Length: 156
Ligand SMILES: Nc1[nH]c(=O)nc2c1ncn2[C@H]1C[C@H](O)[C@@H](COP(=O)(O)OP(=O)(O)OP(=O)(O)O)O1
Ligand code: NA
Ligand code: NA
View (cartoon, rainbow, N blue to C red):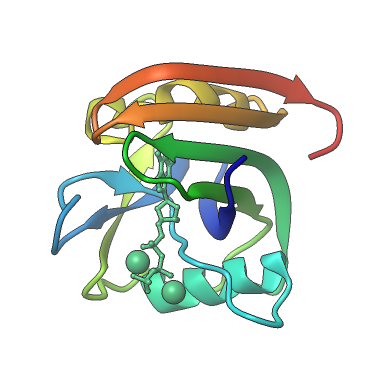
């Protein structure tokens, strides 16, 4: 059995558009995603998600709603990534480029799947339908899924 590390992912989903951020530097630059990062000691997962959204995009929100959980396994990495996925309930400011992320709005008929993580093609449609989900994806490298499971759930 493997150990897991907690991460968050936040999607600012509005009726006609979604905010994504492009990772700018280091390895993995060039992919659009929601905003998030590692949960820290003592904070709830939801509070860590709010913190990462603020650090990465400049947006503050009072509340999130949990929509899914996705476990990622990478060949050659013994530690699993346990990603808790949230959507914002309202936003109150403008996104700001940081050094980790360049935020950009996308219309919901222009979701940039080819420039997102491959797994997003599977679970993000559920997110768009306002469904809740559990997923697992095993990757070889950054691009190749070797195994995955995805299930709609009534409770995350
Ligand atoms: N396959 C995948 N699909 C997806 O949709 N999001 C993924 C993903 N793999 C990783 N992520 C997300 C989870 C999280 O939001 C982010 C990874 O977090 P990071 O390691 O950048 O966190 P931190 O910035 O806290 O870490 P440090 O560099 O240690 O500060 O990418
Ligand atoms: Na962090
Ligand atoms: Na990061």
